[PDB]
Amino acid sequence: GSVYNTKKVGKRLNIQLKKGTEGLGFSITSRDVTIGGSAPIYVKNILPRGAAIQDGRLKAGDRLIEVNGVDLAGKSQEEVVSLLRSTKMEGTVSLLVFRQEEAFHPREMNA
Image (cartoon, rainbow, N blue to C red; front, side, top):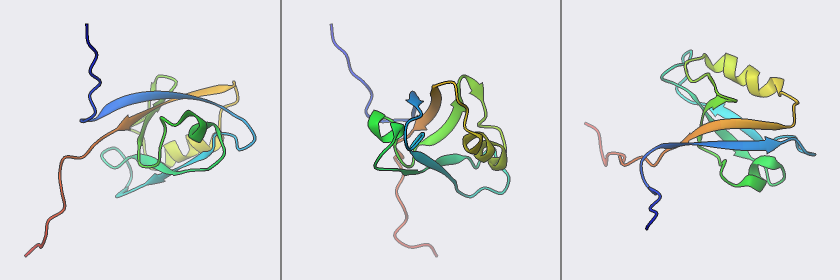
C-alpha cells in the first residue's frame, strides 16, 4: 500500500487546542472584509507560547472556517471575531481551518 498526502490544493484541518497560560495562543485577522462571507478570517498571529503554536498545524494565514462543527464561514467578520474573543472554556477547542496553497501569482505590471 501507499499513502500520499496532497501537499498542494486547499484542505481543511481541525486543530484541538487546550487553554493554557496563553490561552489559545493565536489571534485572527480579516482581510477585504466589507461584512463577511466571501471575505473571511485568517489567523493573524501565532504567539511563541500557547496551544496553537504547540500543535503546529495551526499557523498564521490559515483561514478559520468553523469551530466544533458549527459552520461560521458565512458569518460576518464581527460575529467570528466575537466567537474567538468570547473564548469557550470546556478544555479543548476544536477549530477547523482551511489551509490553501495558492497556485496563482501576482502580475508583473497592470496597465
